[PDB]
Length: 259
Ligand SMILES: Cc1cc(C)c(S(=O)(=O)Nc2ccc3c(c2)nc(CCCCCCCNC(=O)COCCOCCNC(=O)C[C@]24C[C@H]5C[C@H](C[C@H](C5)C2)C4)n3Cc2ccccc2)c(C)c1
Image 1 (cartoon, rainbow, N blue to C red):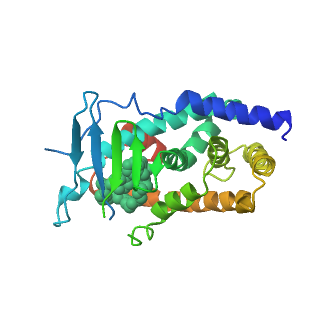
Image 2: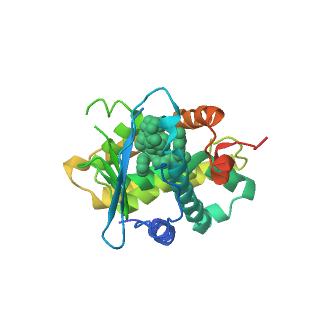
């Protein structure tokens, strides 16, 4: 019930997503593993049927608390590469000046990573199911006090379509107010078009009373996700200051100069 401009925009996004989101994590390899606030266990299922499980340590006032950071840095880096590839496939993004492309990716990389991670989040088991890797929240309502955690549960409950997730990714990517953006007006117009497309998609394909105000719920979540991004970017920089762990790609995305 959309225009073709809107149908072609969704098709392009869905194409970009299909080409650049390794949903089985098959090519995530050669990552570090822990030596032999909220914590996760890590499970690795081998192609032969073997399983390794890692249960994290407790806080004893020592560096043990950072044992998973190298692994997570490798996972995040793998995800960020996918997010960068996604953006670069999209015509509207490719047409932007390269400095704005970089500014938009620096601004949105965390948000797009979290949106992709929500599609592999199992809310029944509190587990991000990443192909052969599984990350399980360690033991309740104290968990939902963490804003990013409550975000994942609340977004999962909306039961969004693939198309709605990829429009969320576009709206986040084309945010006209990230630091360093110059083509503010063009980006702002592109964002509005993606939001209108999402509003119309929901109107045409979700007539049920449960999906009343769904478009507005999604937009409020995107606003909330940007606020969480700012908080978590500061958390990353504090930990990096006392315990370096960011990969080069993470340093580039989060504004660490190397000097
Ligand atoms: C320090 C840090 C910060 C950022 C910003 C990143 S990032 O953006 O570049 N990648 C990333 C990847 C995935 C993220 C993820 C971030 N935020 C989530 C959402 C679920 C968790 C919400 C936050 C919980 C509160 N804690 C923190 O805010 C910082 O805790 C540092 C101290 O750690 C204590 C021991 N806990 C761990 O070792 C486990 C991890 C797991 C993950 C989040 C958090 C920091 C890292 C990465 C270690 C705690 N997910 C979803 C998801 C989680 C696990 C597996 C798969 C998906 C990085 C890399 C690092």
